[PDB]
Amino acid sequence: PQVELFVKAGSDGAKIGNCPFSQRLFAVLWLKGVTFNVTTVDTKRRTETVQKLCPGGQLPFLLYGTEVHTDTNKIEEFLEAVLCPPRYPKLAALNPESNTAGLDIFAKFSAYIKNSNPALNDNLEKGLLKALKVLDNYLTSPLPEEVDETSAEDEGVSQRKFLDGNELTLADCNLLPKLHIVQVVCKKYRGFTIPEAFRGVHRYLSNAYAREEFASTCPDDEEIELAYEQVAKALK
Image 1 (tube, rainbow, N blue to C red):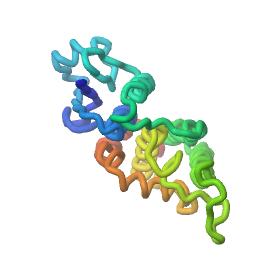
Image 2 (image 1 turned 120 degrees about the vertical axis):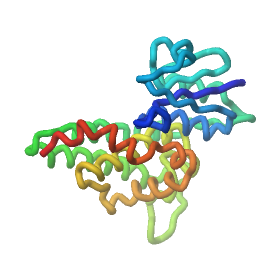
Image 3 (image 1 turned 45 degrees about the horizontal axis):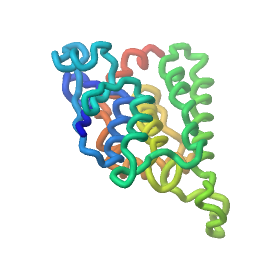
Image 4 (image 1 turned 90 degrees about the vertical axis):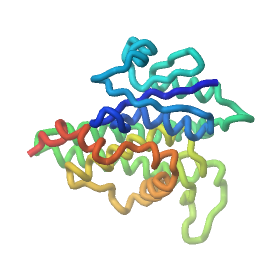
């Protein structure tokens, strides 16, 4: 069954570019354990093949068998439904709220990073921090699998590695590529780092960077910084 992911190329026309949608599906496919290929597209210099496969030009897209699929959310839903046990793990979260935890962070970041009004900087940095804190509280809330298991010193605190438990799920595949952009960009252009006191978020990121599915699908930091340079530099 042939599976080829087409993804956004970076500044050299070849390496992985900044696209958290590309990276989400790359990670889903890696987690499924299916055999697949990844082909980068320089959208300024498209191949005759890519032009034929996807006239509409959407990116990312997926060639599966002879069918071309577009729309990241739909492509992911398709993959989860078609790549099924026993050959491939189900990657859907068990707890619905894992699928919404921290979904606001990226738009708070986008406002913060596009803002060029100095009087609103602190408001927008607050908005971002508040959204990150709500993610932190999700990551430290025990989930049903952890029911009544603890230690005297950390009662009512979750020990789990990722959003929905100790395995990576589709929820992590959506969130992590975006959280990665937020970190990289805000360090470079805002002097901002996530507070050390968000221990849940910190642990989450520590565990996520330790996983090739996330770590090996990340664009180079440089690609992410270049992608944001024009809109991030406007604030003086």
